[PDB]
Image (cartoon, rainbow, N blue to C red; front, side, top):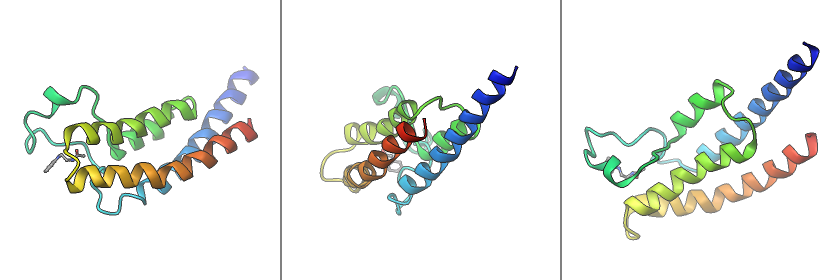
Length: 121
Ligand SMILES: CC(=O)NCCNc1ccccc1
């Protein structure tokens, strides 16, 4: 139907906007601490601690599959990256501190993205 095509066009455009957001957010992790999933070969007990792991590569996979239906779904995955890190790692670690910085610097990018998504429809 024409309606389904129009809907798919909107999804494609959302994916394009979210791709830009994702690149901007990942730029705020220059150490690439959150770039890949935590390896069970390196951290064997990780899944005993964290029930819903997330990372930028996994987000990018879901993104390119047009698996984010709205910004809220995207933000919930971004939030997992930060919240998981701030649970698993203690406050005086380079990991926790990177998560704080990513949260702070990313809020700016997400504040604008929320307005843009509301604007464009
Ligand atoms: C994203 C995150 O929580 N990173 C810290 C915990 N994972 C870790 C993996 C290899 C070596 C040291 C630590």
